Image (spheres, rainbow, N blue to C red):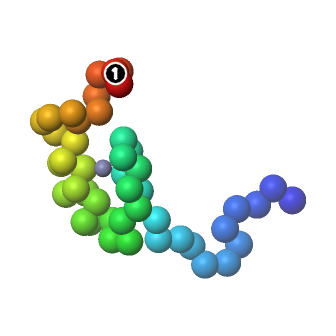
């Protein structure tokens, strides 16, 4: 039985680059901004 969430869902809104968990999905939406300028983690490097 390959099933997923049988019971309650899950509130986990992690970022993309930094992959930071944000209890609130909205808060993250705005946070993502931080990744728009300096060391945005776009071009492969480091
Ligand atoms: Zn982030």
Q: Which of 1 and 36 is in front in this view?
A: 36
Q: In this view, does 31 lie above or below 24?
A: above
Residue at x-position 21% and y-position 33%: 39
Around disc 1, counting alpha carbons within 10 Å, would you say few (fewer than 14), some (14 to 19), or many (20 or more)?
A: few
Horizontal and vertical percent position of residue 19: 41, 50
Residue at x-position 38% and y-position 56%: 20
Q: In this view, does 16 lie above or below 3?
A: above
Mark 1 = which residue?
45
Task: Name, please, the residue furthest toward the top.
Answer: 44
Q: In this view, does 23 lie to the left or right of 4?
A: left
Q: Is mark 1 within 8 Å of ligand 1?
A: no
Q: In which quarter of the image is residue 21?
A: bottom left
Q: Nearer the viewer, residue 17 or 25?
A: 17
Residue at x-position 26% and y-position 66%: 26
The number of numbered discs placed on residues in the rendered structure image is 1
Residue at x-position 35% and y-position 25%: 46
Q: What element carries label 1?
A: loop
Which quarter of the image is occupied by the N terminus? bottom right
Horizontal and vertical percent position of residue 3: 76, 60
Q: Is residue 38 above or below residue 27?
A: above
Task: Name, please, the residue furthest toward the right.
Answer: 1
Q: In this view, does 23 lie to the left or right of 2?
A: left
Q: In which quarter of the image is residue 6?
A: bottom right
Q: Is residue 2 above or below residue 35?
A: below
Task: Name, please, the residue furthest toward the front.
Answer: 46
Task: Name, please, the residue furthest toward the left.
Answer: 37
């Amino acid at each position: 039985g390959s099933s997923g969430s049988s019971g309650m869902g899950e509130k986990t809104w992690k970022c993309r680059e930094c992959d930071m968990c944000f209890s609130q999905a909205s808060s993250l939406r705005l946070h993502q901004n931080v990744h728009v300028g300096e060391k945005p983690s776009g071009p492969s490097s480091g």
